[PDB]
Image 1 (spheres, rainbow, N blue to C red):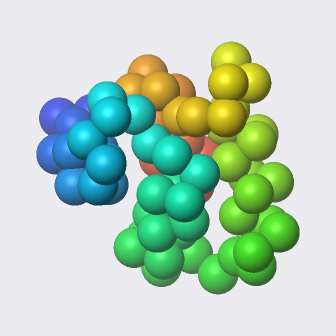
Image 2 (cartoon, one colour):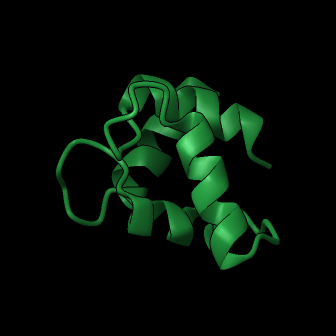
Length: 69
């Protein structure tokens, strides 16, 4: 799964910063077909933001994709 999530990660990283941004995560939610509100998405983002840096790392991305349908 992680090998496929590596491809998805590169797809989802539109900025190409080496991580998933909050706005990029909002897109991910849509792209995964998950029904969240503007607030709910930010809540889940913060939940997956273990480092509390305002970003989702690759390692945390692999966790997020398992936690997020």
